[PDB]
Amino acid sequence: RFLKVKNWETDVVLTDTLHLKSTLETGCTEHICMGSIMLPVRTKDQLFPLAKEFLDQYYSSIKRFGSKAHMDRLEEVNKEIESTSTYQLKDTELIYGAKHAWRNASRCVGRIQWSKLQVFDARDCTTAHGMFNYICNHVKYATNKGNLRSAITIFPQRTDGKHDFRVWNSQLIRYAGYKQPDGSTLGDPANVQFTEICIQQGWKAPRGRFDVLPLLLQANGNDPELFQIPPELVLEVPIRHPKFDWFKDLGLKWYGLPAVSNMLLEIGGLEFSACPFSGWYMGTEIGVRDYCDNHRYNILEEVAKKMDLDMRKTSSLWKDQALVEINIAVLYSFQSDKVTIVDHHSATESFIKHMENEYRCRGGCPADWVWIVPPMSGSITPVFHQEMLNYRLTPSFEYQPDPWNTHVWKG
Amino acid sequence: RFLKVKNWETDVVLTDTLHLKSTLETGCTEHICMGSIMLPTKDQLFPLAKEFLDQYYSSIKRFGSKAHMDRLEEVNKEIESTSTYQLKDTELIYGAKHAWRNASRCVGRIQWSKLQVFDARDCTTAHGMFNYICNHVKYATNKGNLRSAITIFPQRTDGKHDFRVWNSQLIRYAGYKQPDGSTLGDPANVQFTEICIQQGWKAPRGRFDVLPLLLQANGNDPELFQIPPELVLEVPIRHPKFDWFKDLGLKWYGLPAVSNMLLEIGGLEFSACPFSGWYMGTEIGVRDYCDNHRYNILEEVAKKMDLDMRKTSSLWKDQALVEINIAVLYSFQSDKVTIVDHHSATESFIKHMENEYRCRGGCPADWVWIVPPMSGSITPVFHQEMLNYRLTPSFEYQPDPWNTHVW
Ligand code: HEM
Ligand code: HEM
Ligand SMILES: Cc1cc(N)nc(CCc2cncc(CCc3cc(C)cc(N)n3)c2)c1
Ligand SMILES: Cc1cc(N)nc(CCc2cncc(CCc3cc(C)cc(N)n3)c2)c1
Ligand SMILES: Cc1cc(N)nc(CCc2cncc(CCc3cc(C)cc(N)n3)c2)c1
Ligand SMILES: Cc1cc(N)nc(CCc2cncc(CCc3cc(C)cc(N)n3)c2)c1
Ligand SMILES: OC[C@@H](O)[C@@H](O)[C@H](O)[C@H](O)CO
Ligand SMILES: [Cl-]
Ligand SMILES: [Cl-]
Ligand SMILES: [Zn+2]
Ligand SMILES: [Zn+2]
Ligand SMILES: [Zn+2]
């Protein structure tokens, strides 16, 4: 079967065949689309087909499909699964697997970069202290004094589900949030629950607006342990505006390194429950989402006040005007400090070139429009009028529930 | 099977049961989501009529009543005999309002029950259609105090006698390919404009020429009519702060009126059913003015603002976009022509959606269309999960008639 997608701006039509390789389900049916829903211990039996599907893909990618080496590897994995109920990936397979999980990540606008991913193999890690060292090293490598490099660190795979490695933080670097007795929040409201957990575990909170959270790390299914990332490894950018000299006095800053630490990496049916990965920011992630969501730093009003915009009616578009200036300040600030950042026009233009290339060379590029279109100025970016098809390819990154909900406390 | 929708901003969770009444297909499967794709007999007719009449009688608290049964009986007899049936005026009005209520792509549905329905099923000729449409335009326009309206022409019979408005909207601007290679006017309307000239329209050849209506009655070849110029309310676009903005020579029309969709009620198909409301400002200032394939005015505005256009990261496009949208709203408000900004409209839609969940068990909604084309995440619909599904009565896309009509 062939599926067509049209671009309503250019009239360019593309043909998707890659969707035939999709396995997992979307949440949608013939009767209902769940495209805007955010969230719509394997046996041997189910494991070997998943392993074989992966190894076939890997050997095809290296132009060794059906070779003795391919056949020998299938046999080797078969025997390992029948004997030990699981198997280990070769380092080459692990690298290929992590790169493809990114390539397949339908919500990621940054995928033009997918083949440039540094993979740190942490499968020899056994303790939380060991995890801490690996993570510090990832942060230092990825930060590279502001010349950001994409990276992923991969800890040991799931075994029986009672020995999982987990990073309890949602991102490696993120700011604390503190709910006050008067119902206001100091710092980042997104992180109040996790901050309370850290405090309960023994973290001495500075209780300021931009306190870098400690790492809370679980190895081999043990209770998690707290570690502070060395402050000298955490690159941050004070936010200022190129024309408005008062912008700096809002006291805003953000960290340079976006590093997702709460997702599960699936490769050939194996599950890597701790696999922190990082790239660099698109400006709107900070300037729109983190600063301007009502449940985040929520700075729109203050900014608009200082610009002396007419705030008596929404039709003056004061919110829109303030939002653009905030986003200008974020890009200006990162660029001035020589910290890698991409604006939403550049990122979406590059994504469309990536997507078209993937259609030609791969037969498709699964993409989630809801997440791919930036959260401001949508229609003036080239992804808005691009039709997309969303489907699930493996290897993949998957959502997992926060570990405080599932963890069995040992004491 | 019962479904939850969460708002990620307010944590409020709503439960949808209405989707279980959904009938038509979405285009998605368990394997693939097509949520961002724009276009994803006597035997057949009675179940559809019954489904509709059942919902109608339930709405007036008379389900299972003698009047309910009698009407079902009457409609059955009429279908068995004539291969179709006619709606009562009450049923026609109910069906039209519910087609709007069910329109998953419409952010304006808080207004759904306040729709003026003009029954034009007695219309027989294209000149008759012209008169009805002029009256609709005048009523809806109401000297700038716009009122929602729909005008419903005769239903489809054998499909060889369709009523159709060939225009995509009742009021829209012509587009003309230039010897230059450039396009003058609205590039969206180049093909339809050519058809109009081919059918004998004397084109003025300007940037904002209101297109004539091409009306098709009873399956006949369409005929040309000009809307009286004095019935077409337009707004010149100026800016409250930038004196030079007026010098761009921009204007737009006050009345947004869709004329190319098919209204389905109780299995009956109304192929000509122009309907109109009032604008949300981004429709003009973002879509019509700034789409690359439309009037595409971003560069000119940015230049007049003297922004740094050397690099995308100055956000010059975003700055000019906001200013264009400020000018659209200011202009309509100053001339006392109804318009709603995207903050106000989306706030209203959220309130509407909560009402619909509580009173009706759900509200089908297409997030891709509901979220405004600028400043998405600062509006309350962005963080609102929505379920998209198809309920009838409905408005449906139908192919442009020149691809279909046999002359
Ligand atoms: C190199 C620069 C990168 C940029 C500019 C970028 C950009 C983004 C953005 C803007 C989002 C959506 C966030 C939002 O809508 O608020 C996203 C999501 C995501 N990206 Fe990337 N990305 C990059 C690198 C990476 C890397 C290295 C990986 C993995 C190796 C990755 C995998 C993902 C995944 C799995 C998601 C969905 C996350 C979730 O569900 O929470 N991206 N990306
Ligand atoms: C009264 C004020 C109204 C407002 C502010 C409004 C708003 C809108 C907007 C902004 C869109 C999408 C346009 C875009 O995304 O570029 C839309 C679509 C739509 N609306 Fe409304 N609307 C109104 C009245 C109506 C009425 C009166 C009806 C029918 C009786 C209607 C039915 C529809 C339908 C069927 C669509 C999808 C059209 C298509 O597929 O092309 N709306 N509405
Ligand atoms: C409920 C829920 C589900 C889900 N799949 N993801 C989330 C978190 C969404 C999220 C929020 N802030 C930040 C991110 C990171 C996106 C991101 C990731 C990377 C690697 C680089 C980059 N520039 N940006 C993701 C929440
Ligand atoms: C666990 C959790 C709870 C909560 N209340 N909110 C969140 C964050 C939800 C959230 C808010 N803004 C942005 C995002 C990023 C994902 C995202 C979501 C949507 C709808 C569009 C888009 N472009 N990107 C996520 C997470
Ligand atoms: C290929 C295609 C499919 C489809 N379903 N609709 C379209 C037209 C989209 C479209 C473009 N401009 C304008 C509209 C009208 C939207 C609209 C309608 C009404 C009644 C009021 C209001 N404020 N706005 C719709 C095109
Ligand atoms: C027949 C036809 C052909 C063509 N090439 N373009 C069009 C216009 C396409 C178009 C462009 N921008 C906007 C719309 C309105 C519908 C719309 C679409 C989306 C994706 C989001 C949103 N908020 N609203 C429609 C129509
Ligand atoms: O305070 C805890 C939250 O940060 C956490 O629940 C995140 O929202 C979650 O991990 C999703 O990324
Ligand atoms: Cl956001
Ligand atoms: Cl648009
Ligand atoms: Zn879907
Ligand atoms: Zn947000
Ligand atoms: Zn558009």
Image (cartoon, coloured by chain):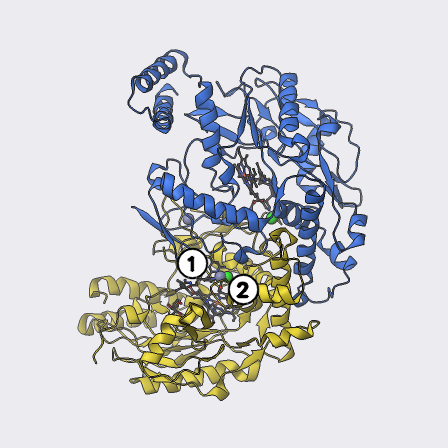
Chain colours: A yellow, B blue
Quadrant of residue B376 in the image? bottom right
Hey, what amino acid is under mark 2?
A: Cys
> Residue A77 versus residue B53: which sits nearer the camera?
B53
Front in this rendered view, residue B25 or B140: B140
The answer to the question of whether label 2 and label 1 lie on touching residues, with beta carbons closer than 8 A, is no
- Quadrant of the frame with the C terminus of chain B: top right
Q: Is residue B318 left or right of residue A205?
A: right
Of all residues shown, which one is farthest toward the left? Answer: A83
The quadrant where ligand 7 appears is: bottom left
Q: Position of residue B87 (x, y in %)?
A: 44, 19
Q: Is residue A209 above or below residue B131?
A: below
**What subunit carries mark 2?**
A
**Image quadrant assignment for residue A21:** bottom left
Picture coordinates of residue A100, whole percent (x, y) = 42, 67
Q: What type is the residue that disc 1 sits on?
A: Trp
Q: Residue at x 34, y 86 (%)?
A: A130
Q: Within the image, what quadrant is residue A125 found in? A: bottom left
Q: Which mark is residue A292?
A: 2
Question: Is residue B218 among what the camera can see?
Answer: yes
Vertical order, B262 against A118 (above or below): above
Which residue position holds label 1?
A: B8
Taking A307 as reference, is A13 left or right? left
